[PDB]
Image (cartoon, rainbow, N blue to C red):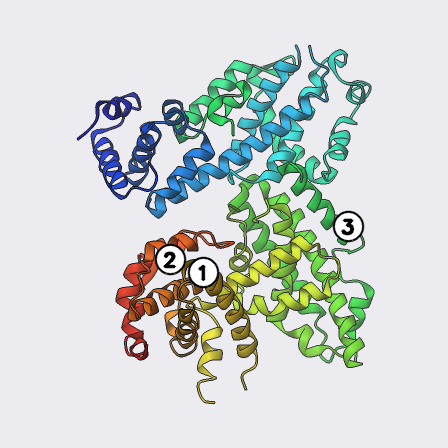
Amino acid sequence: FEEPDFTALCQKLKIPDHVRERAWLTWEKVSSVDGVLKKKELWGICIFIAAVDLDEMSFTFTELQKNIEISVHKFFNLLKEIDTSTKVDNAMSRLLKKYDVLFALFSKLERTCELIYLTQINSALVLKVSWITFLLAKGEVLQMEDDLVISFQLMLCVLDYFIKLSPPMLLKEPYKTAVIDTRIIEVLCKEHECNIDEVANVAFKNFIPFMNSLGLVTSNGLPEVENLSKRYEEIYLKNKDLDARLFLDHDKTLQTPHTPVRTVMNTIQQLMMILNSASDQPSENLISYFNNCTVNPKESILKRVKDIGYIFKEKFAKAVGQGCVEIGSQRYKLGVRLYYRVMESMLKSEEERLSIQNFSKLLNDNIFHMSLLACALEVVMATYSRSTSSGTDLSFPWILNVLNLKAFDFYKVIESFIKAEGNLTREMIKHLERCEHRIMESLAWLSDSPLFDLIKQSKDRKSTSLSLFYKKVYRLAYLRLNTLCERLLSEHPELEHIIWTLFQHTLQNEYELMRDRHLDQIMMCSMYGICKVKNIDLKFKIIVTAYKDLPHAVQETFKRVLIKEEEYDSIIVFYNSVFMQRLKTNILQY
């Protein structure tokens, strides 16, 4: 069956035989299903799929792109059509993220250069050397591969270095009459809404040490452009990544309210407003409430903060880069500034309501403090990340594993936090609400979770935390169930309430099915399970396609579902083996 053009492409990418024969088998099963269908683009994608699942990348992703002449986003889009394995999805995800971040940074770099150098050692030269230098500097200090902020501050340091190297003649007027001194790193931090202390730490701890490892290749300040270019190529060929040097030629392979970096840099200043009066220590009023307690909690509170900042900036560095313990430090400080601030707002607001000053059960509750702290930290960590409406591994629920805090417990504080801090931006509020959504949809239903005891200790007839939670889950569950129903079942509106009854029945009387599973999986199975006993043609592929268009739905939710303990399959396999096993004698009634 193997068309020659395919075997040709396979050869140009040095594809091994097992990979060739699996790239082809994939092309067979894909053309077999139709709905997508030049046909060369799809071939390389099949090759790429084969070379990821088989752990045999004999080619760099840029090489593949050079051959099927596809754009990065286009490649990604087309891949969503194919029933690719989760492992491919991870691969393309990481690659998509890497590209977007790199593109943003490079765009920002090239944009800034045209405003520093009047156009014509010269501007074109420094752009090349700054970018490749940064490219190498990035790889040494950062282990994230998609952290916009630290990368950008790093890039600002690189830029700073080469502006001074530049003769002031070809510099534009702010910078020209400025290198004649250290005002350059200030001007940038002003022009780009960056903290001067954040940048200076990166320069001292990361950028400058790195440059000092380039002495053998630098003459007259300037590193050898070509030696670095070769040093980068060595790493590009190794990761089989994308050749990021190509941005310099505006290479086609890499062509596609505020551009991505200024966006995130501004929300950071928005956090600097909110905290422009909060010390990293309990204020005297905070200390008042402490002293006005039955048991003075100040000892346990100052210690918890110390203990957590240790586990934090360590874990931070484990994920961001070992040479970044100090930025983990200056992130955590911000969290503490917020944390103490909100705690003062809470206590004060609580005496306006309770007319007392002894808040001793509250202030000595260990779970309450960890909650409030994890929450202040999250606001901070999210302020520093690329907005997740494709986020990161520092994204929620990263902060929950650091503090060893159960998601349910974390959820209970969100509402009071938002209200206690009247200065949270709408975006921060919206992000916290989405955090609550994840706890509701899956996290609180994890195997080790207080929730299942609130449920067990309600299987009798004092339950109130359990009821407000269930009321919030239902709202989420029905809202999702309903947009799905209107899209897929206009012609049978009588089914919706029926499904919802089965959905409710499961969350309530079969909760031990949600254990380490996802709410939307119980939703999708409920639609299907009912549609079948009432003989409506609604196959899972249809259900699952509609599911993807939901606000924050991810493919892994239907591709990877817990069947037996430590056993993951598809939602269909889940439907038949487990979901129908427990609910057989309930869907009888319908």
Q: Which of marks 1 and 3 is nearer the N terminus?
A: 3
Mark 2, Cα crowd under 10 Å, few <14 / some 14-19 / many 20+, is some
Query: Could you tell me which residue is drawn at 54 percent across and 60 percent down?
Result: 400
Query: Where 335 sits versus 324, above or below?
Result: below
Labels 2 & 1 near each other (Cβ < 8 A): yes
Residue 572 locus on image (x, y percent): 30, 59
Mark 3, Cα crowd under 10 Å, few <14 / some 14-19 / many 20+, is few
Residue that carries the numbered disc 3 in the rendered image: 273
Q: As drawn, is 204 to the left or to the right of 61?
A: right
State the residue in front, 144 or 538. 538
Query: Where 568 sits versus 194, above or below?
Result: below
Residue that carries the numbered disc 1 in the rendered image: 484
Distance from Cα at disc 2 to Cα at disc 1: 8 Å
**Which label is found at residue 543?**
2
Query: Could you tell me which residue is drawn at 27 percent across and 72 percent down?
Result: 581
Amino acid type, label 3: Met
